[PDB]
Length: 52
Image (cartoon, rainbow, N blue to C red; front, side):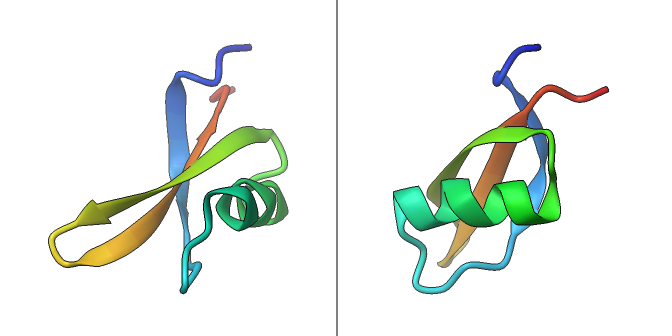
């Protein structure tokens, strides 16, 4: 169980760090952390969790 893995992405705009972490658990139930990062031009909510 490491939160060092990306599980996927969550569509969160505007992307708040805490909201991202929250929406990530909605999409990916085994997600623990979510963080907003800019990729390209838009901000993506990256869902961290343990991939199993």
